[PDB]
Amino acid sequence: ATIVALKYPGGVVMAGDRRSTQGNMISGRDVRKVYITDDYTATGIAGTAAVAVEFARLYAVELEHYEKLEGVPLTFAGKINRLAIMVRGNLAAAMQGLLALPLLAGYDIHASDPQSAGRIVSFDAAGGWNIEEEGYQAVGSGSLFAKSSMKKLYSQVTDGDSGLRVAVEALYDAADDDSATGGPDLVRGIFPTAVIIDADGAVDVPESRIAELARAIIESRS
Amino acid sequence: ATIVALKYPGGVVMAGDRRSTQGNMISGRDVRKVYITDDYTATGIAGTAAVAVEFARLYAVELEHYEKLEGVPLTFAGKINRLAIMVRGNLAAAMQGLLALPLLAGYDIHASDPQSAGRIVSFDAAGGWNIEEEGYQAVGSGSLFAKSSMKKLYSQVTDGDSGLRVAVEALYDAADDDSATGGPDLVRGIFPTAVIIDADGAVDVPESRIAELARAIIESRS
Amino acid sequence: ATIVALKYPGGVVMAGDRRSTQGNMISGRDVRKVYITDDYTATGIAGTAAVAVEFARLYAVELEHYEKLEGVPLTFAGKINRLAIMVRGNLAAAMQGLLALPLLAGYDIHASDPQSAGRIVSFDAAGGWNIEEEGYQAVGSGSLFAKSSMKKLYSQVTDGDSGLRVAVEALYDAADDDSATGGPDLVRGIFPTAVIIDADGAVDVPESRIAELARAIIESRS
Amino acid sequence: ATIVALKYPGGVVMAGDRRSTQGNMISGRDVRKVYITDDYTATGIAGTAAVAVEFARLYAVELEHYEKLEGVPLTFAGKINRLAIMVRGNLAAAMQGLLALPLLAGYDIHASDPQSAGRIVSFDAAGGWNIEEEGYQAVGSGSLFAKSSMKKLYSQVTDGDSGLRVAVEALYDAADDDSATGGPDLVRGIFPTAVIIDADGAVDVPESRIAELARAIIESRS
Amino acid sequence: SPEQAMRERSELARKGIARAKSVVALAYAGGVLFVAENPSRSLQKISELYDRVGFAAAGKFNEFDNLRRGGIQFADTRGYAYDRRDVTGRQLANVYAQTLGTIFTEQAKPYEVELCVAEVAHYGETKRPELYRITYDGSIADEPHFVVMGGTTEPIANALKESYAENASLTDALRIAVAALRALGVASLEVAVLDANRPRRAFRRITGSALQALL
Amino acid sequence: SPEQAMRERSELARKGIARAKSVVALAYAGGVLFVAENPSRSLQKISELYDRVGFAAAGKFNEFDNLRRGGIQFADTRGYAYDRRDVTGRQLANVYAQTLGTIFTEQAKPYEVELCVAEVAHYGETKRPELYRITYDGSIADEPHFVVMGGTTEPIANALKESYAENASLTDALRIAVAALRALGVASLEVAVLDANRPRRAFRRITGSALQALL
Amino acid sequence: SPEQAMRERSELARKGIARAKSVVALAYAGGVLFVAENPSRSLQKISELYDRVGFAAAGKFNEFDNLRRGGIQFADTRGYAYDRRDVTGRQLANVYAQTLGTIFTEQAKPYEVELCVAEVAHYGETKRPELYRITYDGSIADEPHFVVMGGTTEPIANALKESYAENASLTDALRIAVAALRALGVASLEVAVLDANRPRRAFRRITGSALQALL
Amino acid sequence: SPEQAMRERSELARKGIARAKSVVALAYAGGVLFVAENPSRSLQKISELYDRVGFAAAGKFNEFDNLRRGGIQFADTRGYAYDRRDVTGRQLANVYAQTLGTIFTEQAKPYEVELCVAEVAHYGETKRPELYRITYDGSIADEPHFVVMGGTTEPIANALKESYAENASLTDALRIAVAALRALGVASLEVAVLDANRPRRAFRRITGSALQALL
Amino acid sequence: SPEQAMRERSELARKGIARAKSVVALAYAGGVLFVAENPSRSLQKISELYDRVGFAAAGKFNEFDNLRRGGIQFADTRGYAYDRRDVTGRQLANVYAQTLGTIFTEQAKPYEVELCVAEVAHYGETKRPELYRITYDGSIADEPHFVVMGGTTEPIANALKESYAENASLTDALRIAVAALRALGVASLEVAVLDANRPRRAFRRITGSALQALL
């Protein structure tokens, strides 16, 4: 399990792997771990799937409920506070073993500079949150390898396509260096899913672009 | 994590480092640990960040709530009592491992001598509080080194700039003698944050002055 | 931590040290441990400071509340019963480690003989109380040394000054024989605090008299 | 701690030692352990003082409350039942270590034979009670030695003075054979306290008679 | 208007007790004798509360049945708490008065009952029998010789005031009680006594051929 | 209309107390003397609340019996809490006033009782006796010499206002109290005193041949 | 008859508010200005609810004091829950309307108060001030320029309808408000403003020599 | 009809307070002086609430006794919570107003009391004394110089409005207060002062020979 | 008499709704169009309950605001429990009818509201819009084409019965609705639609220049 997210001028990208493992045996091959909560942010949870899907659904439901009740969407700080409270409320279950660490990436429509409106937030096991400002952040088992790869590869990010390519390459490096992370599948045609958030909203990247990027990266590495 | 505070004629200064470490790996490089609760006092908490930010926000909210309800600000003794109660109420979580030791520095506007109106209060893990009167106090992992440095360097404190320089030098010594404390960063341009409280209120020290002080100290030590 | 109290004809004296130690490291140098609850008695608590100050404040508040409600002060037996109940109610916290053993000294205005109206009461960890009648009692870590010194020195007590000198000498002996007890400080000018209770009420001994007594004792011991 | 009680024609006597020990160190030298609840019975509790005084006060208060409410004193069986319930209700605290074993001696005014109206009742740790009929009973740490001494010395009991002398001699033997029991003090003038209950009520034995009896016993043993 | 409500409740209670039959309780040389007009045998208006205490009532069966059950529970709990010898009829009469007063005050319909508590001396001890009467509103009183309740009690009260001599035998007391109640065979008559000659339990029921032989 | 309800409740309470008998309490040279008209011996209108406190009441037996039990429980709990010497009759009178006011306000029927609390000095200490009177609505007052309650108290109040001298002996005080109550042998009379000469408990009952010898 | 009870409650509330003094709130070029007739200084009819929200009321002091305390607690809890920027005066006005309606419906006496909630724009942002009025029955309304409450408000309403120009300065707004209230020195006048020029907290009190210099 | 019930409750409260005696409280050069008409010594109408706060009331003793106890508990709890210097008489007056309003609204009988809260300056600090008056319905008000309550207060109000000069001495203030109350020796007079010259506790009782020497 | 109370409650509710303004809801070729007379912009009489459900009401603002909040909570909880596609407007209309009936029965004042629930087809599925009307007493009904509520609805009901053609465009439907409401510019008009062409959420607000261009 590895989820990466980096900031590019005018938006933010988010991607994750598609592998679920029960110990050392592979259980899933195309598991989806990146979800869209509402128009201008997406979340990704690494850990137990049973807690991850529940957290995603509950976060989306709470955001929609508040928006319907008050008539206006929550501010970014309010969303961060709600997610932090949700994470903190599961500390006992995390101690038992039901651990889920989410990653939040969104676009701030109430920012003076649209080019620097992208935000990346990481959460701790105890509920603490920190706003990422180095331009990238990764979570999961292979987070360290992906973070090092992004540290070296962030100099080539200029637009959305460059950021997507860097994210795919970081995921490939994490899968190469970690046995719990699943790389691109050229036999079954399974590729990581990505979400791009910009001023127009959050959209889902088509599988064709990710397939071409993965094929190009594999050819280059050969 | 190291936070220092010393008393100078006519006010009080407060500063802290900008390092967060998850065990032995560095997680943050510009973490802010000094906060302003209201006009005439500032607080600094060393320990778990998830508890530190919550404590700062709750203390500020309680002070503002009391001021709005009664129409007058709380006395310094009342603020100390409230902070001590808040610290004491978290003893079980501290025993489990969620420990947070705050440091309180403020200015007493109801004192006969304005030059001696600065106050420094330290809190224990069990909720006990003691008013500091040696002129300085430090908390955190590298508190001992900073306290020794301030013991030797307190003879040169005459005004606000001298106190700020002494605090920065003590933080530098603590970072030198402790691997969990982050010193000044000349590559990324990260410097410790400081807050100065005087008769006119509590203000935030600009980063430029701290940068010049750190550069001068580094040049002198070379 | 050492608090001593002895009886002299026409009153009672009470004194304690000014040292707080966190394990083996010195944390405080002028900590006050003797407090005045109301007009005709004073109390002294040895142990955890966070519990000691709370106990002193709560005892004073309860006594004042009863006096205001009923219009008359409580009898000495009632005060002893209230203090014993307060001590007994903290037995679980004492078992965990939050132990506080108070010492009560007061003047009985409802006694036939004014010269024998002084009272000294000691309390156990389980809430049991015993009225001291040997003429002296000490509590704290160095209680045994002070008690032996008072056993030898009680023959010279004739009035208030003699009792104060004997108490100061006993505190000096306890500090000499115990590393957790702080003796007189001739560099920083820190001296133990004393309270004298007589028919006119409870008053605080000025620091000058204690300083002269300590200097005379030090000169004699040289 | 040792409390003895024996039956003589026309009444019953009760006596106890005056020593309190905190482990192996002596804490008290004239501790009183025999108390008078009401007119025609007295009680003595051996063990923790903090529980003993509380039990004595509570038993006296309950007896007085019942007498005031109903207008007539409780029967002896009712008093035994109340004391047994009180002892049984403290079994958990006794298991932790707060053990208190009381001894009850009284005079039955509703008996056909006034000469055989004396009663001695002993209580167990679980609340069980048994009416003593051998003519004597002892409780405390040195109960066995005192019981053996009374077994040999009961043949000389004819009246109140003989019973008092036998009780004092048994206490002296228990103090001789046990280091936790305090014998007569010829230096400080401390002697055991005794209570005599007869048809006229329960009275306190003056210290002079006990002093003469102890001096005579000491002279005889020399 | 509290006065009107109290008056109406008192009138209702008096009318309810007035239609009930008469039960007579008196003390003789061997304790307290209870005589009642009771046709059925399944229903008993005379019972035993403790070793030396007795119960008697007149009115609606369920109300004094509940009062009797509560009194038995109170007596047994008090005896188990302190001692069996610490229970007296005075406590039962007091708690009955309090309960009847509370019912009269804070209930929709006042209780149409009238209770009597009779206590005798303990075995081997000489003491005079004590009788207590409790009314519907909770009033308590002490009666030295006899207690008469239920219905038109004036003729029976007069007939027991006159021609009554203390220290009488069981047979003479029974004859006097029956004569006063008439102003009557084995059937429709309930007879119970509190025999102080008994060691522990003083309650006894006289029924069958023994009752016929008595009168 | 609260005024009408309050007036009717006050009238009901006054009529209830007016039919009750008169009980007289006065202070003499050795404490406080209580004299009451009580025919039965099982029922007592005079009791003891604490070591130096006394109780007296007139009206419905159950109501002041409950008040007496509550006062005893309060006194014993307060004595066990702080000390035996920290209990005074002022606290008992205040709590009785509050309880009677609460009953008068938030109960269907007001209590038809009138209580008096008498406290004496502790042994070895000189102080004048203090008497407090509490009415049905919870009113409290301080009376220096005597307290008269129950029924037509005007003639007894006049007879104790006149021909009364302080510092009198027990015999003279008893004679004056009996004379004022008449305006009366061993039977139907309840006599109790608060003897300050006693070390701890000052309550004493005078009955039997001693009462006859007294008057 | 619910209609009669509702009519009587409305009449009582209207009579209660009618005897109260008049408080005037209006919006000028720099926020919202509050002017009230308040002789004492310990009692304040104008307060601050949050960073950009204000409070104003007229009527019985305790009722709107309680409402103010509840509003402050609600605002602080909501700010601590989600964020400080997620609190608006609309939520406070809605909860106040619900609370006043609940009081009017399910309470013995309706509240004789009339509240106004005024919110201003956040620092660095341009937006027009919003004023809300809540009546005794819980009615809510939106007023564009000014809100007038308390007593005979018709002359002041006319005087503020006429000769009122938006975007006015603080001095001119204060003079117009005082002139309309008269139809008046430092004493007996309460003046507060919502200064949008302030970074975080927009509430300010104008008292002393500054108020005298203003007018 | 809420109007009729409110009118009847107000009339009942006014009639209850009107029969009570008059208590006068005024401020002099050294604090606040309390003078009351109180014959008994066990009952006190003047008390101390905190270090610098005072209490005064007139009416039924139990009601303001309960209010006093509640105020003391509130003051002590607030002082132990935040600080001893964070307690002011304004908070006590506000909570008293709320409690009296709640009693007037949701109780069968309104409280027939009238309270005054007087606060003085802390030692070493100069500030003018503040007096607050609370009525039966919960109304609150601020009085600059004197507060007069209880009974026919019009003549005393006139006599204190006229011939009253601030900054007066204790003796002159006592003489003026006694003269206004008459329009009176050591007995039947209660005198208490709030001495700001005292370091921590400003409450003092003047009784005995000192009171006689004063006047 | 339940009949009289029910009649008076119904009359009160009818009079309350009769003074309210008229809100018109109708279904066109692309969903359901809501048109309301609403001068203020802070207050909204038209809202969204779920993805394909809509809300509309007329009357007292707080009552239907509370009903709207409860409906939103119910819808969200039901969607989170089973699925988002398992929520229909029929369930919301039924729970609203039950809640309104319970309020009408067991509350002091009946709710003066009239709600309408409009549901549209899911994206990619063809189905006719369904409208439900709920009255103050909890009555439920199904209306095929249009729902008219609030005030004198007879002329608008006639004007929408006549000259109404289904499958009309948004512009024609808006013009017909405005014409029937008149029998009216951007201000004082609230317009909302349920656009079935939208993939997930069908609620849309038409305000500003778009509304002016529409009509």
Image (cartoon, coloured by chain):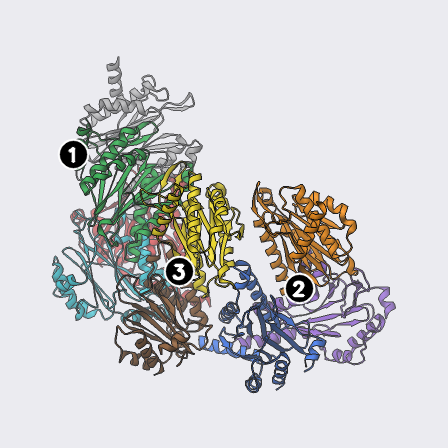
Chain colours: B green, C yellow, D orange, E purple, F blue, G cyan, H brown, I red
Three-letter amino acid code of the residue under disc 3: Phe
The 10 Å Cα crowd at callout 1, few under 14, some 14 to 19, many 20 or more, is: few
Residue E137 sits above or below residue C40 on the image: below
Instruction: Give SS at disc 1.
Output: helix
Q: Quote the CA–CA distance across marks 3 and 2.
A: 46 Å
- In the rendered structure, the residue with mark 1 lies on which chain? B
- Tell me residue G205's x, y (percent): 21, 59
Location of residue H76 (image quadrant): bottom left
In the drawing, what numbered circle is on residue E72?
none
- The residue under label 2 is E67
Examine the rendered structure and indicate whether residue B71 appears above or below residue H5. Answer: above
Residue D208 left/right relative to I110: right
The residue to which callout 1 is attached is B212
Q: Quadrant of the N terminus of chain F?
A: bottom left
Q: Which mark is residue H74?
A: 3
Residue F169, position as x, y percentages in the image: 61, 80
Q: CA distance from mark 1 to mark 2?
A: 94 Å
Q: For this view, does G41 lie left or right of residue E71? A: left
Number of on-image labels: 3
Element on which disc 3 rests: helix
Residue placed most toward the observer, C124 or H157: C124
Residue B55 visible in the shown view: yes
Of badges 3 and 2, nearer the viewer stands: 3
* Residue that sits furthest to the right in the current view: E213
| Amino acid carrying mark 1 in the image | Glu
Callouts 3 and 2 in the same chain: no
Number of other residues with Cα within 10 Å of mark 2, as a class: few under 14, some 14 to 19, many 20 or more: some
Chain letter of disc 2 in the image: E
Is residue E82 something one can see in this rendering?
Answer: no
